[PDB]
Length: 124
Ligand SMILES: Cc1nnc2ccc(N3CCC(C)CC3)nn12
Ligand code: NA
Image (tube, rainbow, N blue to C red; front, side):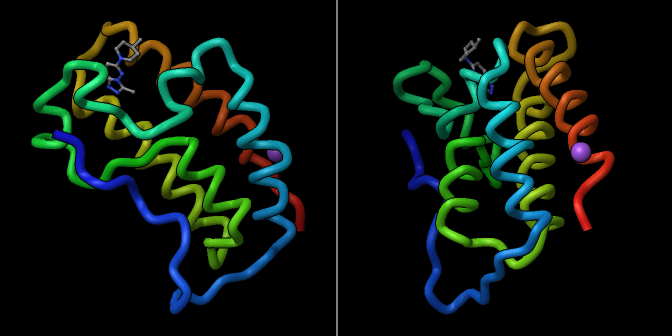
């Protein structure tokens, strides 16, 4: 079955708009989003649709770019590192649930390299 997706709002959580978080939405996320390999990551993994009944029996901190995009648009993060950690969790989840050489893993590897290329230099 599917668990509920990660939260994109939390009224008690402190939030910030920074130049780096603006950039993570305008440049980093919106560039990755258009990549030919982005589509499996644009929404939470649907274990019922995709017939992966063990996905959430294995993956305990799910993350995806649709959640990340909604968090950025909702001003959910305190700083850029928090959002970067969500991207890293998304990539590592894919490596954990699958194995080397899988098509989905090749996709994640390419996106992760583009991601790191984009956050190598951030605005001040
Ligand atoms: C996201 C994600 N993380 N692990 C997986 C395993 C499979 C999967 N799908 C099947 C094939 C893929 C090209 C698209 C959907 N997605 N997936
Ligand atoms: Na950059």
